[PDB]
Image: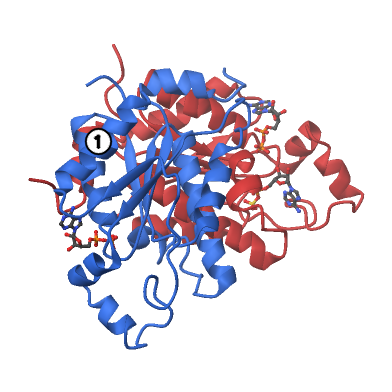
Chain colours: A blue, B red
Amino acid sequence: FHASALTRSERTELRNQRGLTIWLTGLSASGKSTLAVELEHQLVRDRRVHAYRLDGDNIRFGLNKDLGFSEADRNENIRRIAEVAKLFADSNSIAITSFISPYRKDRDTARQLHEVATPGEETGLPFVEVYVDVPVEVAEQRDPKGLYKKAREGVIKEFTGISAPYEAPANPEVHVKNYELPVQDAVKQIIDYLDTKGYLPAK
Amino acid sequence: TFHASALTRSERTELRNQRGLTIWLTGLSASGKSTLAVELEHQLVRDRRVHAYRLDGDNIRFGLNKDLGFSEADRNENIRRIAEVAKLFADSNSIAITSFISPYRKDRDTARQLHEVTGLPFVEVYVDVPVEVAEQRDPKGLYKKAREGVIKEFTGISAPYEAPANPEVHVKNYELPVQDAVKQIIDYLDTKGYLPAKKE
Ligand SMILES: Nc1ncnc2c1ncn2[C@@H]1O[C@H](COP(=O)(O)OP(=O)(O)O)[C@@H](O)[C@H]1O
Ligand SMILES: Nc1ncnc2c1ncn2[C@@H]1O[C@H](COP(=O)(O)OP(=O)(O)O)[C@@H](O)[C@H]1O
Ligand SMILES: Nc1ncnc2c1ncn2[C@@H]1O[C@H](COP(=O)(O)OS(=O)(=O)O)[C@@H](O)[C@H]1O
């Protein structure tokens, strides 16, 4: 019987794909969730790989149902999400996250956790920071849930882009100017990048 | 010309060619949980060709749960988080394999309902050895430290272990080859049709 756990190399070959994390960041209504859902469809369906999205829906009322909006809780929220994305990446799955993650330190913390060697290997796992970029005016014109309106009326306290800052990434792996660009083209810009790094199986 | 709705379990199941579920190991320190987890993961990924992942002390205690100490509020939290992570894995159509002592019936029960509450299968595996067997293995000298009071509230010595009354799989993991134990688990999984067809 095997006494040593599967190595990244054995798992990579046996699962026939690599593991990495795709981290979307951008204003509310920039389209993070929209790109994540379609990106996941193509990866699993079109590319035949294991990919899984982490977002408010499966995190907020589960793993992080105990976190509020305090500085401490906001940091812990990001920390936990990052550790989880890392576990999926370590299992040779492609984790896709779509949290506003407004602060540079939010993404730095997630990147660092991924970029540090894993128990056994000499390297970490790829962390692909995708800036889903739209001017605030574009986000406000979308405002599907009315959040911006309620943000400009204090109904919502400190809202990214309105009463709290969004710190734009200077050097994201993928910068998607997600406006006046069809969703299919934006998702393609992402998949095309992944292919240039050979992060995906043939096709 | 794009998907507005996220992949459904049914579709992810078709596309991934496997079901997702959580195999929860529970038992005393040195009962053999990691050994079983490692070999089980090898067999599921290699021989059965599926996506499975072990959640053990290694990748959890120093990462996601590094902030957790030992107050009971902490041991409950440790278990709760692990259960939620296992569920996400099952939801992704992966077979999560967790190996934590998880001494309290309450925690395992809470973990289970998190899954069964349509829903994900939760296969509770009791990796059972009487305490004298675990204490004679004591590969890391933890039992010796517990006996000397160097480690307090040590499961099975100075803290309780609530054995599962009706676990899906009961492994009498003593004077038993690891291969036979893993086979017991995998065979149970096939009786439930949880795995794709065996490779020819
Ligand atoms: N490339 C795009 N072109 C036009 N509309 C888009 C595009 N991407 C996203 N949207 C639209 O913008 C709104 C916000 O998208 P959403 O995914 O909910 O954003 P976020 O997850 O960043 O809050 C939705 O109405 C969505 O359909
Ligand atoms: N079936 C077995 N028979 C005899 N020894 C075993 C068996 N399974 C595991 N062990 C031994 O027992 C020790 C504890 O196993 P381990 O898997 O680390 O336990 P646990 O993870 O439950 O604390 C190890 O030294 C291992 O080699
Ligand atoms: N007080 C303690 N009780 C039990 N295990 C302990 C204790 N202190 C340290 N350990 C170590 O931590 C492992 C148990 O950790 P877990 O499996 O994560 O336990 S659980 O109860 O929270 O599920 C044991 O194998 C042992 O190496």
- The x, y position of residue A31, in whole percent, is 25, 57
In the rendered view, tell whether residue A161 sits above or below residue A55: below
Using the image, name the chain to which the residue with label 1 belongs. Answer: A
Q: Which residue occupies the foreground of this view, A151 or B63?
A: A151
Graded by Cα atoms within 10 Å as few (under 14), some (14 to 19) or many (20 or more), the crowding at tag 1 reads some
Q: Quadrant of the N terminus of chain B?
A: top left
| Quadrant of the image containing the C terminus of chain B | top left
Q: Report the front residue among A184 and B174.
A: A184
Which residue type does callout 1 highlight? Val
Total residue callouts: 1
- Residue A37 in the image, given as x and y percentages of width and height: 24, 49
Residue B152 visible (yes or no): yes
Q: Residue at x 31, y 36 (%)?
A: B194
Vertical comparison of B47 with B135: above or below: above
Left/right of residue A152 with respect to residue A10 in the rendered view: left
- Seen as rendered, the residue at the extreme top is B200
Q: Residue at x 54, y 50 (%)?
A: A108
Q: Is residue A116 left or right of residue B8?
A: right
Q: Residue at x 74, y 51 (%)?
A: B156
Tell me: B116 left or right of A40. right
Dividing the picture into quadrants, the one containing residue A122 is: top right
Q: Does the rendering let one see residue B166?
A: no
Q: Position of residue A167 (x, y in %)?
A: 45, 61
In the rendered view, would you say B123 is above or below B39? Answer: below
- Of B71 and A161, which appears nearest the observer? A161
Considering the numbered disc 1 on the image, is that residue within a helix, a strand or a loop? helix
Residue drawn at 25 percent across, 42 percent down? A39
Front-most of residues A45 and A136: A136
Disc 1 target residue: A44
Quarter of image, res B112: bottom left
- Dividing the picture into quarters, in which one does residue B173 lie? top right
